[PDB]
Image (cartoon, rainbow over all chains, first blue to last red; front, side, top):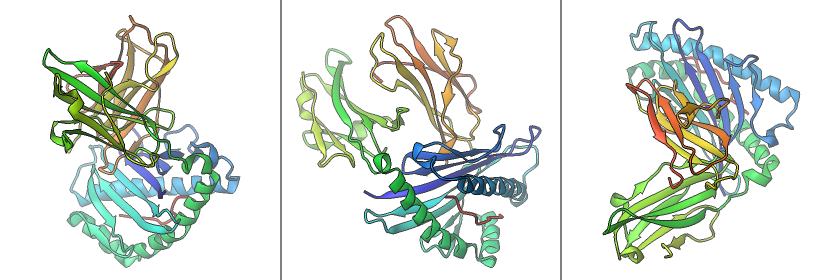
Length: 276
Length: 99
Length: 9
């Protein structure tokens, strides 16, 4: 299958309570593998997956230096953003960034990403061409001009096409046993009367990896999206994920309902029904 | 400007009374990131609850998993209690084996 | 492996 690497930075100001907290985490697909937290007793890039542990002292020292450098940069960026939005120094604000690379099933660079937000709203994004920018507002346009002048897009492109891909491939190899293993969902349908004339059918998917899945109910072969309650896919804590989809049906019509499950670990999509 | 947390309370493995398991409270879709989560056993705060490293979804909203080992029974009740700048008062979501 | 590129706003 296809794979991706992503880093997520969050920088949060907290006037009156010290310098902004900076936290960085790195993922391959849905597996976290590093963390850095400037609020740790001894801030260091640390392993969060077993296959990353074999990397040597130069790796960890390098990543730690890079992360502290980033922490400082993002403290600066929070001050700057205050100026860009005419905001006081009394409020707490958040900058976020997510970036990384996507590989196709052949191991080739599918596309790269580098996007940032301010207070939970789009701020600026590297376009798919890895050479131009999309600014969300006039403040981000200032940043865009600075980055065009410094040819930031060029350096980002060299990273995303080069180191990002090479190291993702390296991780994929080292974590072959888990990163390259899809676990199909374990699925079942439950039935609970709501009243004398209605019942809830709940279609469950458990123990699957990666998180991407599709659960839909059909009635007489027709999609019931509008009448389906879908919970957000949620992590189990053992790397796997869980999800359910529920529909309320007339008593005696249960057999007209079928749950359909699509997932990367399944050779073909599954159809299931309630089994009385 | 601000987004209120979605809250789900559930077990890692399907609940079987007497069998050890993990109680999870997953909070998601929220912004800003500061949030207070407690796991409750019969209304009382469980100590030494662990949680995932702060990360976020493609819409920039944050998510955190809070978890603790536990052994379910028929009598004992579990809940998650969440507070966030978007909430006037703590929100309590009760654990339901079938949810 | 993280990117070393500085992004000053």
